[PDB]
Each structure stands twice: as structure tokens, then as C-alpha cells.
């Protein structure tokens, strides 16, 4: 295989608002023959071209003739864009030097067409809304007004809207991974086994997955529960290492999570009905005769618990276990903590703060087996109204509302949170005894979507763990595909600018995304439908932020370089020290949050190596290859720091800075940011 | 596995396990698992074989 003439380019990157970067182009003649190549670039009004070498045409070179061909530009349009340059040779022009063949084959002209991305100005985010309509062979409508433009930014804020029902899980590349007996300490045992147990439910329940990593996990699970023989308590309770702590309760997710699947796992190897009942008898003992018994949360690790220690929410977490077992006097007992939850639902009716994790989880589950819980096919809608990942991400902020009582939506539980949540969402959805063809599906199938677009088995997530929880999302659908969802759904999409688009849905439009945006700074969205059954469509509003924000609570200590380049060698090499902490980090979770990325044309290596060394007595040696993660050690009492540099991949930079700063500490506090760019300029 | 067993020497003690659950701790779970074995065997109608 051969071609003598091949192109090389300068990648800017996904880059800044300014677009005068340093665009060049180089081809090289590996053929011995010195040939002219007439070159130019096909431009458009999509961008603001500037000819550097205006007067002269890149003209003509010889074998291994190196040449650089660099214009200037400064576009207006944002997002990815294909850039079209072309190079071709002309004949009968033996005037460069001696002679010019200019005689290729059909491979005549060197032509190059390059999708490059600009990151717009400021910082990026989105806002959105959530709406359903369900006429039963009738008609219903709704109006949505979609606006929070404060501190507004030029030409940044856009949107779209859709709905879906997809069937036929195509593939499984989100499936595979593994970890095992860890090396640092014994505390990770809790995080090890818990999702590791529900893997058993996955082998048949996909028709795409990779079961044998889970049919080997049985070979692991055949030792998994053995650690739980030891990590239990004699009286019945359970701890990270077990008993020697007598007359108390203990955390009960990781058991209640399994205590059903112990009973799905009491088939291969025999754990008896005595191990489940001793687990149970622990629980009934604690149920007060009158009160919702007092219990305090200070247990062995928030590593496993992204938790704020609410016994009442946990007073439900027993009752899910109680639904598992068919004792049926038990089932009255779950109505006890139900009425403890009835308080917590009046909380979640007003919708101010109940921590948006748990009353979620099991209210759905609570009556999941019975058969008359129509009432609960309502209350999920909150939870799906509750900033759910209709876009298959719960991206990063609260709407624009500073006040004290706010939800678990911008908290330092930082796995990126979009997978922990939807787990216990979809787990609630389609356990329907009846057909859940109504609105607890069309979003359920949304959850199938990006888990089916989450096709990378690296495991280097925004977390480490969390994508183990990405899977049940895929898994439990495996019979949900046995469904029918299609009716006279006729969809009206109208706004104020005399615009109105129409869409429609059916069993074959069931799986059909209907994307459409608008340019309106106004956001105002009436909608109206008909048909039979229910369906939830969805909003999304993208936009930039951070034109120039002020200082705020949070303390981020950063230093880039010795205060200036002031030397020709610099503008390339300078180590950037960062030294950070925020006091409010109290009984919520492990330490998960960080954000460290480069500037537009700036590439790290020793940064790879300085992070590589760091072990401040605890660590997960985690890294993104553009970012850094050693955080669950300890939070903010005594900060710490490092230093790391780049190489200037950007010879020329339109003067627009860059900052990568993340922050989430407490439910009432204001913005609480601290930022600083690179100074060399 | 799926059988009964002689039950004097346990029933003899299974009270005194409960008199003996004071010095060293055998739990209320050891007496009830001992018990739950028994209720399982009680036929619904017969004086089980
Ligand atoms: C920061 O670290 C200090 C280290 O002493 C912690 O100090 C404790 O303060 C709590 C609450 O005032 C007391 O109950 C303890 O007696 C102190 N030492 C301990 C834990 O025995 C402090 O809790 C840490 N966090 C912050 C910023 O309060
Ligand atoms: C639609 C668009 O972006 N235009 C092209 C696209 O066809 C191509 O796939 C891409 C590289 O993947 O280069 C650009
Ligand atoms: C274990 C077994 O019976 N096989 C099940 C089958 O019944 C089910 O329909 C399919 C889709 O969920 O997954 C598998």
C-alpha cells in the first residue's frame, strides 16, 4: 500500500469562543518527483475566513518538501464543523524548478475535510422541564414556559424536545468489567458485593449481555456470601466486619438489597431459611410498639453510604425487605413505616426536602407486589419530574433558585449521579403486575437508551463503581421488551412566534425520537394530544453560563506560574499548583467531586505522573487522562496540593481564558465558587 | 438434609440454652432456628410421619 502525498494538520481541540487559533496544513511528497500542487480552501459564510498568505499561492515542492500553509479565521457558529481544504496538481508548468510530472492516477488531488469543534464562551449547562399528557381516547393539553436567563450570555441558549419508546436492546458493550478482593483495606467489601449480587439476575434477562463474567461472579459469589457469614452479627445485625457491637441496629441496605437475592441465591449453594429469618427477626425486635423507633446514623462508612443518616427513610429500607418475605403479618408492619413514610410523602408532596433518594426507592416497591397501586403509578411522575435524566444525564445545577430547603440534586455525591439515580428509578418502574404500557415505560425505555449508548467497558467513569449500577437499567428491561405501546398519539408543538410543529406516535413511532429545537430566547410551549393510554414527552434547554462571575464562599487555592511568562521560553512550560478545600462536608458521602482539565491548546504529561505518585494515606489511584481523582481520602479540614504543567499546542490564541472549577457542599448555601485562569498572555 | 432428627438432647437443653444464654451469649436466633425446624414439620392435618 502506498500514496506519496499525505496531509497532516493542526488539531486545535474542542476550543474557545475565539477562533483565530493557528490553523495550518502540511503535505509531504514521498515520491521522488517535484510537482506543483495548486491549493486553496473551500470556505463559507459559516465562519470568518482570513487569508494569511493572501498574495501568494502555496505553490510547489519536491520529494520530502516540507511546507506549512496557515491561514487565519474567526468564526461565529458554534459546535462541530467540517473544514474543507483541497490540493491539486497542474500540468505543463515546468517552471517551479526543472520539471513537473503532475500525473497521478485517479488519486489526483489531495483533499481534506475536517470536523473540528469549538467550545463556546463561558461555562456550559442546560435547563429543562418535564411534561406528560394522557387522554384516554380523549384530549388533553398543557402549557410550558421555559425561561431562566439571568446574567445572560451572547447567543448561547438553545433547546430541544422529544419522546420515545424504544424496543430491541441492540447490544451490550456497557456490560463487561471486573474488580475483586481489593488491596488498600478491607472497608471496600461493602461496595464490592452489593451490586455484585444482583448480577445473577442478568444472565438471561438481556438477550445481549455477557453472563459468564457474572457466571464467574458466582464463582466469586461462592465466596462473597462467605465474607457475609463473618461480616454479620451474632444477634442478627451486620457490619463491615461484624459483631463486637451488641445492642444496636446497623445499616441495612446491603443486606436488604441481598436478603431477597440470598433467597434467589439459596439455590446454587444452600443458605437456609434460618439465615433469612434471623436477618428478619433482628428487624421485628426493633419495631417499637408505638414509636417509629429512634435510631442514629454514624455507622462504619459513607464510602458505601452517600447518606445523611435519616432513620425514617431507612425505616422504609427494612420494609422493602419485609415485602420480600411472604409472612403477611409482616405486610401490616410495612404499613407502619409506611405511615412513618406518610410523613415523608407529605414531605415529598410539598416537595421541599426529603433528600430525593429513598422514599423514591421503595414507595414504588412498597406495594409493588400487591396489584392495586395505580396511586403509585402517579407518584413516580414526581420522581421523573424530579430533574430525571430524560436526556440520559442529570447534568449539573439547580434551576436558578437560591434558598435553604432544596433537593438531592447538586450535592457532592459525585459519581455524576445519573446512574445511581435511574437504577432505583427504573427498578421502580416496570415491576408492574399489570401492563405498565402507560407512562412508566416510555421513560423506562429512555433509560434503556444511553445505557445502550454507554458502550465502553473501560470503567474509568466519572466514578469507578457507578457503572456497575448502569447495568440493572439495561437488565430488568429484558422482559419489558415484551410490551405493546401504540395508539392514536397526535402531538402538537406550539410557541409564541406563530410557530407550530406537529408530531405523532404509535407502536411504530413508539421507538421514534422527535427532536426539534427553536431559536427563541422566549421559552413558551403549549402542547396538546389525543389517543389512548399515557405518554411522557420531554424538554431540554441548553445554554452557556459564566460570562464573568464574582467571588463566593468556596476556597480554591490555585497558582499557575511565577506571575508572568516574562521570558521567551515560557508561554509553553509552567507548573500549576492547586490547593483546595471546603469546610461544609458533613455526614453526606465520600469525597467524590473534582474538576481539572486543560486550557484550549495545552497538553499534560508529568501531570499524569504527579497524580500517579499521589497517595495522601488513602487513594483510589483514579484519573481521567484529562482530569484527576484522589478524593475519598478526606475532604477539607486540611487541604493539600501538587503542581503540573503543559505544552503549548496553541501557537496563537484569541484572548479568552479558561477555568475548570466544581463545587457542591450544602443545600442552602449560595454559589460558592473560586476560580482563576492561566495568566500568560 | 430433608429429614427430622432426634430431639431430646436438644429439647432437653433448648430451655437450658436459654438458661445458658447468660454467661456466654447464644442468641435468640439459635433457639428460634431450633424452633423453626419444628414448626416446618408439623403437618397441616396429620401427625406427620
Ligand atoms: C476538623 O478536624 C478537627 C480535628 O480536631 C475536628 O475537631 C473536633 O471537633 C468536634 C466538633 O467541634 C469535637 O466534637 C471533637 O472533640 C474534636 N475532635 C475530635 C473529632 O475528637 C473537627 O470535627 C473537624 N471538622 C470540622 C471543621 O469541624
Ligand atoms: C455532518 C458532518 O458533520 N459532516 C461530516 C460528517 O459526514 C463526517 O462523519 C464527519 C467525520 O465523522 O466529518 C464531517
Ligand atoms: C430463565 C428463563 O425462563 N428464561 C427467561 C425467559 O423466560 C424470559 O422471557 C427472557 C426475557 O426476560 O429471559 C430469559
Image: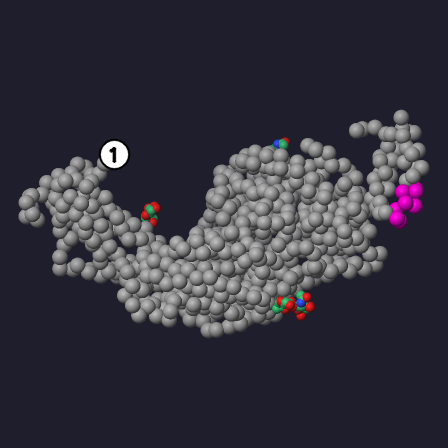
x then y, percent, for residue A591: 57, 59
x then y, percent, for residue A666: 59, 66
Q: Residue at x 45, y 59 (%)?
A: A596
Pinpoint the chain carrying mark 1: A
Q: Residue furthest top?
A: B49
Quarter of the image for the N terminus of chain A: give it.
top left
Q: Is residue A85 magenta?
A: no
Instruction: Sort mark 1 into few (<14), some (14-19) or many (20+) by Cα contacts within 10 Å.
Output: few
Q: Is residue A207 left or right of residue A41?
A: right
Quarter of the image for the C terminus of chain A: give it.
bottom left
Q: Is residue A29 visible?
A: yes
Asked if A408 appears above or below A322 in the picture, the reply is: below
Q: Is residue A660 left or right of residue A210?
A: left
Q: Which residue is mark 1?
A: A1
Q: Residue at x 26, y 56 (%)?
A: A23
Q: What kind of element bears circle 1?
A: loop
x then y, percent, for residue A17: 35, 63
User: Where does the magenta region start and end?
Assistant: B15-23
Asked if A535 appears above or below A564 in the picture, the reply is: above
Can you tell which quarter of the image residue B6 is in? top right
Can you tell which quarter of the image residue A123 is in? bottom left
How many numbered tags mark residues here?
Answer: 1
Name the residue nearer the viewer: A224 or A512: A224
Q: Is residue A382 visible?
A: no
Amino acid at each position: 500500500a502506498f500514496q506519496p502525498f499525505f496531509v497532516e494538520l493542526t488539531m486545535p481541540y474542542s476550543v474557545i469562543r475565539g477562533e483565530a487559533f493557528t490553523l495550518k496544513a502540511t503535505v509531504l511528497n514521498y515520491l521522488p518527483k517535484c510537482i506543483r500542487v495548486s491549493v486553496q480552501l473551500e470556505a463559507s459564510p459559516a465562519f470568518l475566513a482570513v487569508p494569511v498568505e493572501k498574495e501568494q499561492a502555496p505553490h510547489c515542492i519536491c520529494a520530502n518538501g516540507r511546507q506549512t500553509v496557515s491561514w487565519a479565521v474567526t468564526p461565529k457558529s458554534l459546535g462541530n464543523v467540517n473544514f474543507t481544504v483541497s490540493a491539486e496538481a497542474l500540468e505543463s508548468q515546468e517552471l517551479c524548478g526543472t520539471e513537473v510530472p503532475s500525473v497521478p492516477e485517479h488519486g489526483r488531488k489531495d483533499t481534506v475535510i475536517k470536523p473540528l469543534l469549538v467550545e463556546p464562551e463561558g461555562l456550559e449547562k442546560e435547563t429543562t422541564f418535564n411534561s406528560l399528557l394522557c387522554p384516554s381516547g380523549g384530549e388533553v393539553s398543557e402549557e410550558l414556559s421555559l425561561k431562566l436567563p439571568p446574567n445572560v450570555v451572547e447567543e448561547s441558549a438553545r433547546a430541544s424536545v422529544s419522546v420515545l419508546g424504544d424496543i430491541l436492546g441492540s447490544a451490550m458493550q456497557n456490560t463487561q468489567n471486573l474488580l475483586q478482593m481489593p488491596y488498600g483495606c478491607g472497608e471496600q467489601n461493602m461496595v464490592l458485593f452489593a451490586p455484585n449480587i444482583y448480577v445473577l439476575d442478568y444472565l438471561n434477562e438481556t438477550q445481549q449481555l455477557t453472563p459468564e463474567i457474572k457466571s464467574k461472579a458466582i464463582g466469586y459469589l461462592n465466596t462473597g456470601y462467605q465474607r457475609q457469614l463473618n461480616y454479620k452479627h451474632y444477634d442478627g445485625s451486620y457490619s463491615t466486619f461484624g459483631e463486637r457491637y451488641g445492642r444496636n441496629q446497623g445499616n441495612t441496605w446491603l443486606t436488604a438489597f441481598v436478603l431477597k437475592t440470598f433467597a434467589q441465591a439459596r439455590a446454587y449453594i444452600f443458605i437456609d431459611e434460618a439465615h433469612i429469618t434471623q436477618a428478619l427477626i433482628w428487624l421485628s425486635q426493633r419495631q417499637k410498639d408505638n414509636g417509629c423507633f429512634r435510631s442514629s446514623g454514624s455507622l462504619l462508612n459513607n464510602a458505601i453510604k452517600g447518606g445523611v443518616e435519616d432513620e425514617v427513610t431507612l425505616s422504609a429500607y427494612i420494609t422493602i425487605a419485609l415485602l420480600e418475605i411472604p409472612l403477611t403479618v409482616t405486610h401490616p408492619v410495612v404499613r407502619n413505616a409506611l405511615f412513618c413514610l406518610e410523613s415523608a410523602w407529605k414531605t415529598a408532596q410539598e416537595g421541599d426536602h426529603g433528600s430525593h433518594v429513598y422514599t423514591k426507592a421503595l414507595l414504588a416497591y412498597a406495594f409493588a407486589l400487591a396489584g392495586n397501586q395505580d396511586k403509585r403509578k402517579e407518584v413516580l411522575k414526581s420522581l421523573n419530574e424530579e430533574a430525571v435524566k430524560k436526556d440520559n444525564s442529570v447534568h449539573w445545577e439547580r434551576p436558578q433558585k437560591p434558598k435553604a430547603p432544596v433537593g438531592h440534586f447538586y450535592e457532592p455525591q459525585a459519581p455524576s449521579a445519573e446512574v445511581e439515580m435511574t437504577s432505583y428509578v427504573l427498578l421502580a418502574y416496570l415491576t408492574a403486575q399489570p401492563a405498565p404500557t402507560s407512562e412508566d415505560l416510555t421513560s423506562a425505555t429512555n433509560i434503556v437508551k444511553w445505557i445502550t449508548k454507554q458502550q465502553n467497558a473501560q470503567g474509568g467513569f466519572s466514578s469507578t463503581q457507578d457503572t456497575v449500577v448502569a447495568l440493572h437499567a439495561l437488565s430488568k428491561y429484558g422482559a419489558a421488551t415484551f410490551t405493546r405501546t401504540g395508539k392514536a398519539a397526535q402531538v402538537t408543538i406550539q410557541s409564541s412566534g406563530t410557530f407550530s410543529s406537529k408530531f405523532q406516535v404509535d407502536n411504530n413511532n413508539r421507538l421514534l425520537l422527535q427532536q426539534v429545537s427553536l431559536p427563541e430566547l422566549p421559552g413558551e410551549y403549549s402542547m396538546k394530544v389525543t389517543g389512548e393510554g399515557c405518554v411522557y414527552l420531554q424538554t431540554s434547554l441548553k445554554y452557556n453560563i459564566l460570562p464573568e462571575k464574582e467571588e463566593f464562599p468556596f476556597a480554591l487555592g490555585v497558582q499557575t506560574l511565577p506571575q508572568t511568562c516574562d521570558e521567551p521560553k515560557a508561554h509553553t512550560s509552567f507548573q500549576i499548583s492547586l490547593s483546595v478545600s471546603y469546610t461544609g462536608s458533613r455526614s453526606a458521602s465520600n469525597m467524590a467531586i473534582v474538576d481539572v482539565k486543560m486550557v484550549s491548546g495545552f497538553i499534560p504529561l508529568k501531570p499524569t505522573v504527579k497524580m500517579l505518585e499521589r497517595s495522601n494515606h488513602v487513594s483510589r489511584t483514579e484519573v481521567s487522562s484529562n482530569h484527576v481523582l484522589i478524593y475519598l481520602d478526606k475532604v477539607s479540614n486540611q487541604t493539600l496540593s501538587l503542581f503540573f504543567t503543559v505544552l503549548q499546542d496553541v501557537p496563537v490564541r484569541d484572548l479568552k481564558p479558561a477555568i475548570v472549577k466544581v463545587y457542591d457542599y450544602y443545600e442552602t448555601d449560595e454559589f460558592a465558587i473560586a476560580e482563576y485562569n492561566a495568566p500568560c498572555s
